[PDB]
Image (cartoon, rainbow, N blue to C red):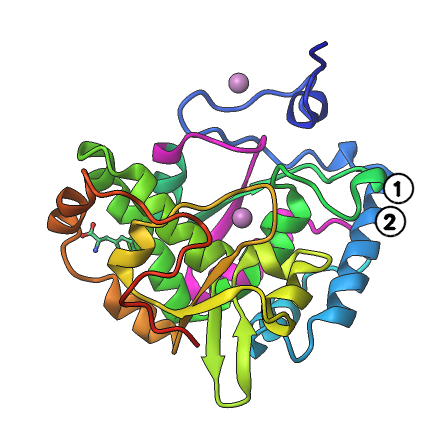
């Protein structure tokens, strides 16, 4: 009744560092099928995302020379990424402990799951994979304000861990880095990686009247649950990456303590103070 999960299967014969969870990218393990899956996913998103993704995202794909036709060589991408904002990507086996993830970000390393979904999982994979982590997350690292936000978020891990507040930080990450929307004069656009790599959440999040699109509010967000197994019911909207960086700059310690005994909002709740857009 129990079978090895995709993370376990993909990593057989491989190792990882016991402290930081990294390994050299195993290039020999990508089959022709992997490159074809990558090319299909990349083509699909590049057709769907113009006028949906924020323009910075599309520019990042191009400036970083993210390969269209094969899984990218992480070292090669790093040459461009390092020159831009002093970040690099590191390969990891899949999901890693929160404190290790934060320590990477604090040091301007972005952890990327090395392996790719199988063609049968083309439409959707639950686990992060190299398409979601690299295509979805990495292009916005060219934006210096976004990159500074990620670094600051990483640095925030130490205080959060010490206060038992990692789930509150996780909610902020989920509702920004993973599933954030950004308002523009041309209309709302997408910056969250979990939407940018998705087959159809990119359509729903902008085109459907169903989800609630709520103005960013730090306390609301850190008090809001999310689910990992369907489309989001609430998206939070920033006005700029600068607004995001500034709103998250103050001391979170009093915010964590006030939220500690609070009843969190459900993934589909509208709070009394929400700016609903
Ligand atoms: N300002 C937060 C750190 C942080 C920065 C950016 C994003 C998330 C958290 C703190 O006091 O710990
Ligand atoms: Co292990
Ligand atoms: Co992600």
Q: Residue furthest bottom?
A: 185
Q: Report x, y in % for residue 150.
A: 37, 56
| Marks 1, 2: nearer the viewer | 2
**Considering depth in this image, is 7 or 223 the residue closer to the camera?**
223
Q: Residue furthest left?
A: 254
The residues bearing labels 1 and 2 have C-alpha atoms spaced at a distance of: 6 Å
Q: Which residue is mark 2?
A: 36
Q: Report x, y in % for residue 205.
A: 59, 66
Q: Which residue is mark 1?
A: 32
Q: Report x, y in % for residue 145.
A: 37, 70
Q: Quadrant of residue 273?
A: bottom left
- Highlighted magenta segment, given as a residue range: 70-99
The residue drawn where x is 78% and y is 48% is 123
Q: Residue furthest top?
A: 1
| On-image quarter of the N terminus | top right
Q: Is residue 87 left or right of residue 112?
A: left
Q: Is residue 81 magenta?
A: yes
Q: Report x, y in % for residue 63.
A: 61, 71
**Considering depth in this image, is 63 or 111 the residue closer to the camera?**
111
Answer whether residue 107 is visible to the viewer in this image: no
Answer whether residue 225 is visible to the viewer in this image: yes
Q: Quadrant of residue 100?
A: top left
Whether label 1 touches label 2, CB < 8 Å: yes
């Amino acid at each position: 009744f129990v079978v090895p999960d995709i993370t376990t299967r993909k990593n057989v014969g491989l190792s990882h560092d016991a402290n930081d969870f990294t390994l050299p990218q195993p290039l020999d393990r990508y089959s022709a099928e992997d490159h074809a899956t990558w090319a299909t996913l990349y083509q699909r998103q590049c057709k769907l995302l113009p006028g949906r993704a924020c323009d910075e995202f599309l520019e990042g794909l191009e400036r970083l020379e993210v390969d269209a036709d094969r899984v990218p060589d992480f070292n090669k991408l790093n040459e461009k990424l390092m020159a831009a904002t002093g970040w690099k990507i590191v390969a990891v086996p899949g999901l890693i402990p929160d404190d290790v993830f934060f320590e990477h970000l604090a040091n301007r390393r972005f952890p990327v799951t090395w392996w790719l979904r199988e063609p049968h999982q083309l439409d959707y994979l639950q686990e992060p994979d190299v398409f979601h982590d690299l295509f979805g997350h990495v292009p916005l690292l060219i934006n210096p304000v976004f990159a500074d936000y990620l670094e600051a978020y990483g640095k925030g891990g130490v205080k959060a861990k010490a206060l038992g507040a990692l789930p509150m930080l996780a909610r902020l990450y989920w509702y920004t880095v993973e599933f954030g929307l950004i308002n523009t004069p041309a209309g709302m656009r997408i910056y969250g990686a979990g939407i940018l790599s998705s087959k159809s959440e990119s359509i729903y999040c902008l085109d459907s009247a169903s989800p609630n699109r709520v103005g960013f509010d730090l306390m609301r967000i850190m008090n809001t649950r999310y689910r990992i197994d369907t489309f989001q019911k609430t998206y939070f909207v920033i006005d700029s990456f600068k607004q995001l960086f500034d709103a998250t700059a103050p001391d979170f310690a009093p915010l964590y303590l006030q939220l500690a005994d609070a009843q969190p909002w459900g993934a589909g709740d509208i709070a009394p103070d929400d700016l609903v857009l």
